[PDB]
Image: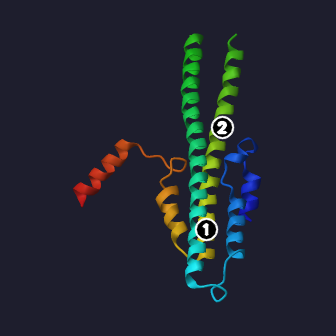
Amino acid sequence: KFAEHLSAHITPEWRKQYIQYEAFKDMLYSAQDQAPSVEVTDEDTVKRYFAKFEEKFFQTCEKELAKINTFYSEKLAEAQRRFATLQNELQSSLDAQKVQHRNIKDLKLAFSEFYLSLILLQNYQNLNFTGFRKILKKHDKILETSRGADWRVAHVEVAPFYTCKKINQLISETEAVVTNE
């Protein structure tokens, strides 16, 4: 069902920029399918096979996360620029008044297109975060490990596509923890 949900909620223009969730599901199937059974091979070849798969899997995770961070950051910087342009265009139109009804009409359109771009970007953030959490839980369930959950905490939960931390905030927060403990 999540593969369906993700597919239905994707912004078509951004399709290639989302977590390749079905490809990860397929990857995990092939890992189970191609798995050498111990009794048909020794304990060391099984460990080496899964070790090899783990490297491929987490390199794909890193590649997917890099893609998501890049796209999100580019879109977020573009959003902050557009918001500044729009606020300046608005103030200049407002000051001008004290016929430009068609001027404001173009701005109403501009703010509408902009707000939508923000909602679409928030959806992309939420869908991608859910996609990572779920695929890593799937990985962990199948491979009977905690490496996926470790990777979620280490790289996804602190990713720029997901969360925002001003260096000043992180400094005041560390000050607080240190002075109080």
Ranked by sequence position, the earlier of labels 1 and 2 is 1
The residue where tag 2 is placed is 117
Label 1 secondary element: helix
Residue drawn at the location 54% of the way across and 19% of the way down: 91
Structural distance between the alpha carbons of marks 1 and 2: 38 Å
Q: Is residue 35 above or below residue 26?
A: below
Residue 172, percent from left and from top: 31, 47
Q: Quadrant of residue 77?
A: top right
Residue 85, percent from left and from top: 57, 23
Residue drawn at the location 57% of the way across and 17% of the way down: 94
Q: On the rendered image, what quadrant is the N terminus found in?
A: bottom right
In the rendered view, does 99 fall on the left or right side of 79?
right
Amino acid type, label 2: Ser
Q: Quadrant of residue 22?
A: bottom right
In depth, the one of 37 and 140 nearer the eye is 37
Amino acid type, label 1: Phe
Residue 105, percent from left and from top: 71, 21
Residue 148, percent from left and from top: 55, 67
Q: Quadrant of residue 130?
A: bottom right
Disc 1 residue crowd, few under 14, some 14–19, many 20+, Cα 10 Å = some
Q: On the rendered image, what quadrant is the C terminus found in?
A: bottom left
The residue where tag 1 is placed is 53
Residue drawn at the location 36% of the way across and 45% of the way down: 169
In the rendered view, does 110 fall on the left or right side of 80?
right
Circle number at residue 8? none
In the rendered view, does 153 fall on the left or right side of 107?
left
